[PDB]
Amino acid sequence: TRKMWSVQESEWLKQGVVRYGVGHWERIRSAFPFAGRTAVNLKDRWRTMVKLKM
DNA sequence: TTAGGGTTAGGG
DNA sequence: CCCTAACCCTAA
């Protein structure tokens, strides 16, 4: 069952991009306690947030 | 391991 | 329902 992204998970990805730059998906995933999210999931999520103005 | 296009399921 | 966010596929 697919799981929608929480606003806390989205803020984690936002700070991880700030602290490490886009494309550093495996580095961002390790800097935050992401449970059930792969680095590819983080990259797809970032594309969604960019498109949704976030 | 990431980028970018393609695919699908679940919620608005 | 069915659009789209959450997925998958794969070159490099």
Image (cartoon, coloured by chain):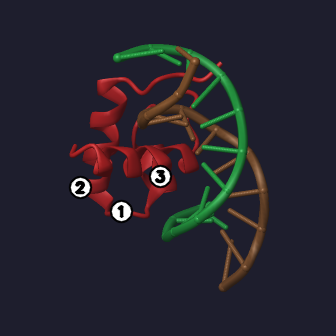
Chain colours: A red, B green, C brown
| Three-letter residue code for mark 3 | Lys
| Three-letter residue code for mark 2 | Val
| Three-letter residue code for mark 1 | Val
What is the C-alpha distance between the residues marked 1 and 2? 8 Å
- Judge whether residue A8 can be spotted in this image: yes
| Closer to us: B12 or A21 | B12
What is the C-alpha distance between the residues marked 1 and 3? 9 Å
**Residue identifier under label 3:** A43
SS label for mark 1: loop
Instruction: Tell me residue B4's x, y (percent).
Output: 52, 69
Q: Are the residues at dot 1 and dot 2 in contact (C-beta closer than 8 Å)?
A: no
Q: Are the residues at dot 1 and dot 3 in contact (C-beta closer than 8 Å)?
A: no
SS label for mark 2: helix
**Residue identifier under label 1:** A22
**Residue identifier under label 2:** A18
Image vertical order of residue A7 relative to residue A18, above or below = above
Tell me the chain of label 3.
A
